[PDB]
Image (cartoon, coloured by chain):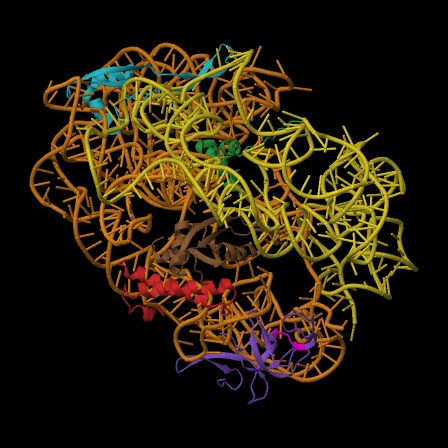
Chain colours: A red, B brown, C green, D cyan, E purple, F yellow, G orange
RNA sequence: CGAAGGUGUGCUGUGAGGCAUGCUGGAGGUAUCAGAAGUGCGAAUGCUGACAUAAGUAACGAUAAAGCGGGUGAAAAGCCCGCUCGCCGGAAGACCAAGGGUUCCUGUCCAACGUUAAUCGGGGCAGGGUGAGUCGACCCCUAAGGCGAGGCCGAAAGGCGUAGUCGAUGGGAAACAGGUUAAUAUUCCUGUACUUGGUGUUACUGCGAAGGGGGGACGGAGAAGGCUAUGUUGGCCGGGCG
RNA sequence: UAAGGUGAUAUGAACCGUUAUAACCGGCGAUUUCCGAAUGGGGAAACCCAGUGUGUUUCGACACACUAUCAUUAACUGAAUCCAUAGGUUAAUGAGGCGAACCGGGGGAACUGAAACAUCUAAGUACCCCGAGGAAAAGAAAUCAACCGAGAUUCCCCCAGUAGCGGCGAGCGAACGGGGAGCAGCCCAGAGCCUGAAUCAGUGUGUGUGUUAGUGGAAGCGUCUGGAAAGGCGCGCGAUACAGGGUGACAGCCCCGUACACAAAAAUGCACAUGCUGUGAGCUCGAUGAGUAGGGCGGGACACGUGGUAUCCUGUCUGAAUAUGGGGGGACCAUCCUCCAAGGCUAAAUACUCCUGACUGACCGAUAGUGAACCAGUACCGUGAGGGAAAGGCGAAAAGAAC
């Protein structure tokens, strides 16, 4: 996914980041409620957030 | 509190206890598991942004973890913070 | 009868606590000894 | 500490030897004196803790050379 | 660089199933391999209230050592040893006897 | 087609020993001649583990005390419910600090723990439970003391100490009644309050400290006098006519 | 590199992948809460409380950054006090702490032995403290030798338990010389001609070699016993590979390996070649280390305990010559020989192993071996420093016993 995400800019990657944070919250609410079933989506979204933050820190200037 | 990134991290789960059910039925209160370092203002902003409901007040308490036994091993569950968020009139979730 | 050990957490932490050991050179030697032995608990603190 | 700033003489350990050759440890201390030397290069009185031998060294060398050595060595005076 | 992959036809060299031809089903990381209808064990499955409740004597396959099976040739019709080589630009497996690519 | 190890038997040498074979065991052993030793145990009030004897003996931990009916249960002297009985009541009652850390409440279980049994338990397992502007801590102030830039001192370590900084057991703002859960409440709900700061608007105005003055701010004993907490009696109300 | 995986207890759920972003491995990166030298102030470690500067704002409040001490350099600033100085603020650079042994230095026992014991021994040991490095220290003769010569320091073997010292008791105990390992000499106290002709050192490039992943890697069947063959019997083959380890008993040919031949996008070490800055060769003139050598007094180190006692260090008091001079050659003197202190630097041979990899063992094999083969510096004991265990083995495979 990093190859696709490198095309995006600092804005439109922050938007992506915030959207994955919203999705992570919603998955957390379903999971904690005990009505998620697909328990593996939490690993998927967390690693996606880590990827977006890595690309942000790369494009910051360092 | 103002940052939506912080708001999306403070709230963790809803509490599913009989005391929580009675509080919701009578006092219009929702009980939540929340982060250790979440402040009352943070919980208020988080509930009133993410759940989209007006919040009257928040009471908080820290729950100490239990020393459980597993085989010969002694483990100590992690402490957690409990938030009693009293809504004004409206509740959805 | 009045026995020897009369606990008081303030007295414990001022006597044998981490900062009491770090205050002096001999206490730092005590910590070095215990850290070389491999103690799980290095002081009375917690 | 009892250290001459000119020469570096310190206390030195040795033995008190009795007539039965009983050796008990002792210290030889230097002959330290705090003296105010009139430095002409700055028109000043500089205080230094100096032994009598160091004072003879100052009299021979000159206070300027001794202070040059001291400030090359450090020795905030 | 493993000589027996997921769906190879193999023949049992040693054990009670010696000479039996089977198709491998799994390649466990402990150097053991499950083969269809070879190492049959009758497990006495206890029932449970929630899921898979029917108990009974169930005959299933246990894992045998990978060194206890050999790749079956089917041209010579015998057990055989596996080697590796580079054809075009890939690591292919080749039958030791009759030097042919699997 | 049965090694080491264990356990019997038979034979064999002057002895430490050797040999053979039945059973057990289920995988190693090792001639001969040389070589090297952590090389031989009955004792050291030897060291470690197991197991006996005393012996089914003493004891079962305040002489405040128990009896019966019903219930659950595989089983009841001990658990639950009930009625009688007895003990404490300046405590054996209620509440805090300290110390402890989940022992708190519910459901379940009785191997071990409980000096007996145990359905019970501060026991095992699981889930639940600790809600504060006003309570306490933090916080602002300091006492004894501690630490302590520069500094003085000292073979090194380091000792002491100035400005200052910590340091309560002391000083510094403010909330009370009633209801409520299985378990929290001056925290939740109801009602009625109080406190201290930020910012706005409005009206008036000389405001300003690391400084000055007041207050904070203080001992022992004794006596009253005025009150209240509280108790008793009477009136009133509700029930009764034993 | 890959057809299998998402660490183990440890099953299950949800998934990911199967010709290449599943996984795994190595290089380089990013993230790296809080305490801890902890460094914004404080503190009963993992907590409490701030200030300044930017940038957001729903006007609620938010996010990031900096803010310790000391040392050195500079700049401004600046008392008593006129110039000055102490001092103050700011800025850059550096340090602080931890770590097993080896190393240098500052201090420094007693038990014990002497069949008591005081000189002596134990011993400059144990221990405390300061400081550095991968090594440290020492090091290029004011050294020995003996009238012949050698030629810096360091280490090993002899000399030699010798000469000596010694309540001549206990004990301590050289050196000269010889054989070896290694071998390296220089610079300043200053001028000229010749100036950067030696020379290291920091910091770039090319080629060979190494480490951090990895590739390939030969050759066996039939039959008997057996639960099972790798065992027996028979007949074959590989071997630059019969090291070792697994596999249902003991396998060269089943597996993983081994001999052997190969491999790096990236990082980096080692050698050469090869750069930038900067340190400056050679000849000639000179000069050539003073509160120093030496001495009185008191101690100490030298194998040497003050003795007839040379030499070395210095706490105290003194104190020359200075190349036509001075030190040493074990009291002291004369001659002779030899060297030139009172300024520095310098690889190798030497010492040790917290840690890393490979290999070995007439080393232990669960009361042994580390205290710890196992969730051990744990449980447990103590205020604390500190002390400190017990505890391995089903089976080839859970096929761990449906009913």
Q: On the image, which quarter does residue G251 sit in?
A: bottom right
Residue F80 point in image, percent of width and height = 73, 49
Residue at 49% x, 64% y: name it.
A31
Residue A21 point in image, percent of width and height = 38, 62
Residue B75 point in image, percent of width and height = 57, 51
Front position in the image: G40 or G207 = G40
Q: Report whether residue D59 is seen.
A: no
Q: Is residue G9 left or right of residue A53?
A: right
Residue G333 point in image, percent of width and height = 32, 14
Residue at 50% x, 57% y: name it.
B24
Taking F34 as reference, is G279 above or below it? above
Taking F117 as reference, is G108 above or below it? above
Q: On the image, which quarter does residue G69 sit in?
A: top left
Q: Is residue F79 left or right of residue G62?
A: right
**Magenta stretch encompasses residue C12:** no
Magenta span: predominant SS is: strand
**Magenta stretch encompasses residue E61:** yes
Q: Report whether residue E68 is seen.
A: yes
Residue at 33% x, 70% y: name it.
A3
Taking F27 as reference, is F111 above or below it? above
Front position in the image: B79 or G352 = B79
Front position in the image: D64 or F209 = F209
Highlighted range, magenta: E59-64
């Amino acid at each position: 996914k990093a190859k696709e995400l490198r095309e995006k800019s600092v804005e439109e990657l922050n938007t992506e980041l915030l959207n994955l944070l919203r999705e992570q919250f919603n998955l957390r609410m379903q999971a904690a409620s005990g009505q998620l079933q697909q328990s593996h989506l939490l690993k998927q979204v967390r690693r996606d957030v880590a990827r977006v933050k890595t690309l942000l820190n790369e494009k910051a200037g360092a | 509190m103002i940052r939506e990134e912080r708001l999306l991290k403070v709230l963790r789960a809803p509490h599913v206890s009989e005391k929580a059910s009675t509080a919701m039925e009578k006092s219009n209160t929702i009980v939540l598991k929340v982060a250790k370092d979440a402040t009352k203002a943070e919980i208020k902003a988080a509930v009133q942004k993410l759940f989209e409901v007006e919040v009257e007040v928040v009471n908080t308490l820290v729950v100490k973890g239990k020393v459980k036994r597993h085989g010969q091993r002694i483990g100590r569950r992690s402490d957690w913070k409990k938030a009693y968020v009293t809504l004004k009139e409206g509740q959805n979730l | 009868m009045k026995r020897t050990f009369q606990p008081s957490v303030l007295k414990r932490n001022r006597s044998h606590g981490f900062r009491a050991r770090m205050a002096t050179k001999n206490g730092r030697q005590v910590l070095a000894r215990r850290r070389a032995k491999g103690r799980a608990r290095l002081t009375v603190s917690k | 500490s009892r250290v001459c700033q000119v020469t570096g003489k310190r206390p030195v350990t040795g033995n008190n030897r009795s007539h039965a050759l009983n050796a008990t440890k002792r210290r030889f201390l230097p002959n330290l004196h705090s003296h105010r030397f009139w430095v002409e290069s700055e028109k000043r009185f500089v205080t230094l803790r100096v032994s009598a031998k160091g004072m003879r060294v100052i009299d021979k060398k000159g206070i300027d050379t001794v202070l040059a050595e001291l400030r090359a060595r450090g020795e905030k005076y | 660089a493993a000589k027996i992959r997921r769906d190879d036809e193999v023949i049992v060299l040693t054990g009670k199933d010696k000479g039996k031809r089977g198709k491998v089903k799994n390649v466990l990381s402990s150097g053991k391999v499950i083969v269809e209808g070879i190492n049959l064990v009758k497990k006495h499955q206890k029932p449970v209230p929630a899921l898979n409740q029917p108990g009974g004597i169930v005959e299933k396959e246990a894992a045998i050592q990978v060194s206890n099976v050999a790749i079956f040739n089917a041209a010579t019709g015998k057990a055989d040893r596996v080697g590796f080589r580079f054809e075009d630009g890939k690591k292919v497996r080749f039958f030791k006897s009759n030097s042919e690519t699997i």
